[PDB]
Image (cartoon, coloured by chain):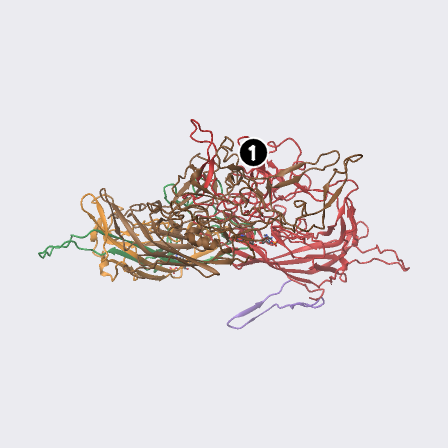
Chain colours: A orange, B green, C red, D brown, E purple
Amino acid sequence: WALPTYNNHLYKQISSQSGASNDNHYFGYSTPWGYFDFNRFHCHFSPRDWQRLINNNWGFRPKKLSFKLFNIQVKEVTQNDGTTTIANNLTSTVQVFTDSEYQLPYVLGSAHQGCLPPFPADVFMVPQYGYLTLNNGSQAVGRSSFYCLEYFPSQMLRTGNNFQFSYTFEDVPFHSSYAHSQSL
Amino acid sequence: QGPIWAKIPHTDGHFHPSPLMGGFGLKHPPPQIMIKNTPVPANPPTTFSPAKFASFITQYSTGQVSVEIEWELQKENSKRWNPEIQYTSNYNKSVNVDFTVDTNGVYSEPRPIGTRYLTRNL
Amino acid sequence: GADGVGNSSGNWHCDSQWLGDRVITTSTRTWALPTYNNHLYKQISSQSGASNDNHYFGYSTPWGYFDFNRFHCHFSPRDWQRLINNNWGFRPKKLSFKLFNIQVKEVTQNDGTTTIANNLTSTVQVFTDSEYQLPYVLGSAHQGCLPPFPADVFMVPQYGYLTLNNGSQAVGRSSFYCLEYFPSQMLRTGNNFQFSYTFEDVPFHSSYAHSQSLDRLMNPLIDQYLYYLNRTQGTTSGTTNQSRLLFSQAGPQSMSLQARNWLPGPCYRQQRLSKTANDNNNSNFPWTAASKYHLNGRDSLVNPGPAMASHKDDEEKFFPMHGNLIFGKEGTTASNAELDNVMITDEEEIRTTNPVATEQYGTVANNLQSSNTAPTTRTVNDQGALPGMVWQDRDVYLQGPIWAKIPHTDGHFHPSPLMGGFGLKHPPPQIMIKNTPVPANPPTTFSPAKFASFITQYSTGQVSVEIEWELQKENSKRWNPEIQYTSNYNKSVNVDFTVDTNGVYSEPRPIGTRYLTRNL
Amino acid sequence: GADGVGNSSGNWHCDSQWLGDRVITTSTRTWALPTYNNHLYKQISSQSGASNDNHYFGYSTPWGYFDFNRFHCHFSPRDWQRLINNNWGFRPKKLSFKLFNIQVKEVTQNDGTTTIANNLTSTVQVFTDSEYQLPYVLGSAHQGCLPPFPADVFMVPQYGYLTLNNGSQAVGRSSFYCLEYFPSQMLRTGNNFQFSYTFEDVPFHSSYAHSQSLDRLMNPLIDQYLYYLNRTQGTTSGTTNQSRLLFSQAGPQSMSLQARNWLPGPCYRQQRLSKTANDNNNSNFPWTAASKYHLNGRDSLVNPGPAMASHKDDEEKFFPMHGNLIFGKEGTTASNAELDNVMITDEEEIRTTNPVATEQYGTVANNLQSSNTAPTTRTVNDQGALPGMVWQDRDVYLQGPIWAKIPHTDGHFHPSPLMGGFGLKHPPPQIMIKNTPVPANPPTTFSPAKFASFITQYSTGQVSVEIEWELQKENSKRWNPEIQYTSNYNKSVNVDFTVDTNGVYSEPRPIGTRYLTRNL
Amino acid sequence: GADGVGNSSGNWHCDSQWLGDRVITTSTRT
Ligand SMILES: Nc1ncnc2c1ncn2[C@H]1C[C@H](O)[C@@H](COP(=O)(O)O)O1
Ligand SMILES: Nc1ncnc2c1ncn2[C@H]1C[C@H](O)[C@@H](COP(=O)(O)O)O1
Ligand SMILES: Nc1ncnc2c1ncn2[C@H]1C[C@H](O)[C@@H](COP(=O)(O)O)O1
């Protein structure tokens, strides 16, 4: 994965174009933060595997999860003349954390882009984080919420540091990997 | 290539909390993992300026990410006598191979793959 | 096992369940047994001058026998699909045989009506050739196996064997076998028969197809470090340039010239046939132009020969003259049936290890080329065995043979039954069965003459057969989906592998086994 | 193994010492690894109508791999001499593989000058195909092995494989393999890679030549007690003497008529070639007149065939049309190089067990001779396998292949790699290696498009390979000295197996293995 | 359960009685 510097390290207020559209009016914010997504099946199942699953099982479901970030490299670039040199910044850090209390607006499960490449050899760019609040047209209300991600405890990592995380899914019914041989 | 799960909105009421796009609806889904490069200030003035700091060193980050998921399976138990329909590739002499990279290395998924191939009774 | 009249001597066990590492199939059927040969051993032989390559000599016994050397005896279609689509291979392990719920019925033709009644005191005789002292008549694709469909009742086959013969006559070293000279268990109604068998170590079958080819085995990107000679004369063909010896280093380019490590399997060329009855020669050549062998001045048709592929790429219409196994559709004359009435088997998965049946084998030199002599090439149509050769064996089909006894000789080569399946030194033994003769009214005066007046009667009961199968699990890092067997989801007339309007089970197509792919 | 930047992750172990019963060779070399395919998996196939017997389909991976399937990777010339001149045979036993002292360099073309700098935080990925789930691309005599000379640095070969194909197109059963779908160890500078392997039971190689001949096996002094027929007509040819049946008892005199117990090995006649470019036919016949085979309607050249002798006595100039392995001298075009630029291998030690490659095999009868019919003789140019046949296998040379994976099929015959060496069901696994992709400057705006902007960089480090060899000791009661390999004591230009004026190592001649003699 | 020809393999249980908290119905038919 690769991660740029979004919003130029700035939190920016975003909203709808002054009279561009009505049913598309919205209000929210844009953060300098990226995020990881793997809410697609092809992130985990190779085609062949999907075939094994599909052709043999009445159903299935998730159980556990282990997340790991590692082999981190921070690169700083300079446009001196007409050529870009890229070099190592060894003393530079990166910040990670997980919304485990669900205090941040859940922006996943909306079929957005930026998930893990179906093909393992493919490198991907990490999506930028943005959220929507409550709005009256292009304007906002008083009960609108502003969320700063710097106000969350986060682990800072240098090169050679890493990030660990484990999660356990809840009791959720098996999916229907079957079709009824009878009719209502 | 579809969605897997979706957070169930924290409201007073739900009906059938299955995500409408399909998949698993969770009260408490896999949490969001935030990541960002820490700001690195560039050359500061020998004189003290209160103004917001805006001069930064441009830089990006790269690394690996790993994700391990355990899946519970519900096994097939049918007394159907005749063979059921299965997903399969075309044995036919073909151009490119399904779910593969091409002449200039670009992975491509030919068709959307369902899940309902085996048959159960009502 | 000994019980009463009004008490069943067994239950109906017809099921199958999987253990991920093995599968157990249990199969029960109802059987009926007549009185063969009228309780007589009869000498049989060939018609006085009817045919020559079909001359034979042997005997006919009053004994029946049980057969289940067909796969569909054990695997339902659905099961066969589970096996086929998931396993690198498989093999037999154990066996349990059971006869029970026996009923002996005697019939009488009084006037013009046949009454059938119970003979409770009548018996039946069973035994098993466990020392293999009787001629093994199984594994010859005969009929009389267990019905593919469990609901179908079947008739038990009669036992007969062949000996050594000189034409229609016999030799001095010919063997006569009496089955009454074997200890056998006699059963009344409420008695039953038990038997257990353990298969020997026999290699897993190939439930796979190679994803590579014997010739496409190397690295497409790198050149070899070995050199070959590719130019004998062709040079800078201008002035004073007759001939020269030039050598090229193997490249991905010279892909069929590179040094090799292995050979394809053996071959015995078959004649090529087309399904379109007009591509062929307007002659009748299924005998005069087909491949065959001869023992003791007797021509025998080499029906299924060594494992060779049926057709080359972009054809699929040309099948070897009997170079493969053929199954007859449900309801089809045993005598000259149409091509639309039979099912021919395609062996196109072994294209990568084996030569094509109809095509040549290769090219051999047969002269000493020089400036005086032009180099001669001879097409090889027949190839014995060679160090370095590798091959695959014939497939097995849902309705194909399972095993075959390996002949007790001084020598064998690759003891795999040519019709396919598992070759066993000591296969599941033969289970003989016959109704005990019941004499009719005897004379008040003593007659020495052979007794010939018997009460006509047949028997019926259930038979159960339980086999344990070891599975070889699939372990592939293939990224893309593999080809699987499946039914047509299309709106269809009748359902595949089913009974019809008037209750008749029918198998639509022959089912192979090689759907999953493994590398060489 | 985990250490720091300024601390080496291993040492230089390049040595060999003998234990009289075994020998341990250790070999270390420096290696360099580029970025193949630009970090991309590319589908490759044959040129749209370029060639037919060379049609192929497969893929190209960004992965490199390690190879040491050459003998000179382990044995210095001097060592090979010690082995060759003293041992009835030998074989592999154990193996230790090590990667270390890794350095990742990234390069930049700024203006017209390339600066190369350290990327300390960059990684590299290694793993081993120990379950043999990847197509085995070794044992095909490819290039990119470890340099014969320890001082030579080498480039690591790129990985590519071939699948199943119908012409330039592919089939449905074709397999795509992603190497990113394998668990692999990632290494930074100061990390290292460890691996150990144990060879299977594989027969000792023949480091000997038979001192007897299949036909000169009996007692020269005594006559047999068996009789043969040597006269059919020739009698006291005077009066009334047309024909008669006469039998002679075998004698040392009738030495090639005596009853025999064994046969020579199998054969597949090759075309005969002369090194003098004027004894040959003035035609270009390296393809139309050479021996070959065909799988799936695709002709493939039978380069090294069964082990057959290269020439008969008193010749040494006639070599089989590619009937043996050929090595290219140092510095010689991969395209049509002169005969004075290659090294051809003579297989003249197996003259005693094997037929000559260029000559016939023997003589077979093919008629029923009588007074009416004259007896016909047919020259056999191709011989399968026969009970009683014995043979020797191809030699191995200092720069030859060592082992080869035995294809996972239903059948094999004599699983010895045809190019020579040790055939293994489970050979030393493939060791994959590749530089981890390092993305360049990303856009401040989110782009879903495939990432294509990468930092160019290559890797370098050392590799070590330790193999243990079991020796079969010489036990001969031969009185007279045997032939040994030796260097020319003569005043010479350059020294054999050495670097030259401008530092370039060169191997003068191919070295066989059969110098010592054993009896049949 | 295994008996003989001239021996019934069961009896006629057709009754019902109440337990104030539950009721048991037994029913037999030919
Ligand atoms: N994806 C998913 N998640 C959770 N529950 C599901 C899902 N799909 C179906 N259901 C059913 C299962 C329970 O019987 C019911 C609980 O509703 P409640 O509103 O919780 O009482 O909803
Ligand atoms: N169906 C079957 N049964 C037994 N052996 C088989 C079969 N198919 C292949 N083979 C191989 C396995 C052994 O390596 C070899 C034994 O031959 P032998 O002649 O026993 O030394 O034959
Ligand atoms: N290089 C190599 N590897 C393995 N076996 C070899 C080799 N060379 C000769 N042989 C012989 C040794 C065994 O007797 C036989 C096993 O064949 P099988 O087909 O395994 O029953 O093959």
Helix, strand or loop at mark 1 = loop
Report whether residue B80 is seen. Answer: no
Q: Furthest residue to the right?
A: C445
Return the residue at label 1. Answer: C376
Residue type pointed to by label 1:
Thr
Mark 1 Cα within 10 Å, few/some/many (few <14, many 20+)? some
Q: Position of residue C277 (x, y in %)?
A: 61, 33
Most foreground residue, A54 or C345:
C345
> Which image quadrant for residue A67?
bottom left
Count of labels in the image? 1
Task: Say whether residue C453 is left or right of residue A171.
Answer: right
Quadrant occupied by the N terminus of chain C: bottom right
Please tell me whether residue D296 is drawn above or below residue C449 in the rendered image: above
Task: Say whether residue C406 is left or right of residue B75.
Answer: right
Q: Position of residue D461 (x, y in %)?
A: 33, 54
Q: Furthest residue to the top?
A: C239
Most foreground residue, D169 or A53:
D169
Q: Position of residue A117 (x, y in %)?
A: 35, 50
Mark 1 — on which chain does it sit?
C
